[PDB]
Amino acid sequence: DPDRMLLRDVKALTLHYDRYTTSRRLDPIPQLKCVGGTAGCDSYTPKVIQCQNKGWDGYDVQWECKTDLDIAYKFGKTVVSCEGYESSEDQYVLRGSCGLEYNLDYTELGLQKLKESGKQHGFASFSDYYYK
Amino acid sequence: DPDRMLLRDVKALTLHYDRYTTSRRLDPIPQLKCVGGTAGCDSYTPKVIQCQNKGWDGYDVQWECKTDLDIAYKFGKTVVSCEGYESSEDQYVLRGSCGLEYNLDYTELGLQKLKESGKQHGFASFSDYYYK
């Protein structure tokens, strides 16, 4: 009974990159996960995101999800998803089952940094020697 | 016999971050390894370095070791080390046993970039919802 919450009345979510969701019917997944975007998922990733329920439009709960990101990055699409308690159509969901996936995109500043990221210099060092 | 070379007559070395040295008397180690410096070893690392034997000063062979580095980085001290064939005092060394360790330091540009690396922005996204 308590692990059953009406999704539309859940006020807020705090989702972490190193914690898993709760589940029963489905497999646990990261509470926060990069899934694409113009910058991709292989390098910088936020560790936490804060979501607030902004109301209900007749179809979906409206989530505003924010976090501090390095200046080179922003979110593309973000998607919140929870485990409906009885089924996927249930309006109640399993407590703790919500997660977020995001596309990570470059900002305008990020794309300039990317343009310049390849710059290198030939550096010579006169090495010591160690006998072994 | 062939795996025995006089170190002073070895013309050049090409050392790779993902290959191990040869050894007998000692354990194999990475041909190229970061060991300290003002930037440290946890992030960017060169993958290869090219060393040329620049002569003999009466004590040590003089190695000049160079590679292309990202503009934010340079080498602090670098040290070449090979496995002497019979002992640590042997002037012949085991073929393939040479490696290099380096300190990785920030350049002047690197330190400015580091100064600014922490800059962030609060980014809000209005998330879609996915039923499951």
Image (cartoon, coloured by chain):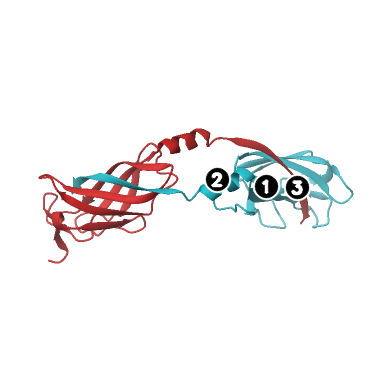
Chain colours: A cyan, B red
Q: Secondary structure at mark 3?
A: strand
- Look at the numbered disc 1 and give the secondary structure of its residue: strand
A1 horizontally vs A29: left or right: right
For label 2, the crowd category at 10 Å Cα-Cα, with few meaning under 14, some 14 to 19 and many 20 or more, is few
Residues marked 1 and 2, same chain? yes
The three-letter amino acid code for the residue at tag 2 is Lys
Taking the view exactly as shown, the residue that stands out farthest to the right is: A58
Q: Residues within 10 Å of mark 3 (few under 14, many from 20)?
A: many
Q: Check disc 1 and give the amino acid type.
A: Phe
Residue in view at x 40 percent, y 42 percent? B73
Of labels 1 and 2, earlier in sequence is 1
Label 2 sits on a secondary structure element that is helix
Along the viewing direction, whichever of B115 and A81 lies nearer the viewer: B115
Please tell me whether mark 1 or mark 2 is closer to you in this view.
2
| Residue in the image at 38% along x and 54% along y | B47
Residue A113 tag number = 2
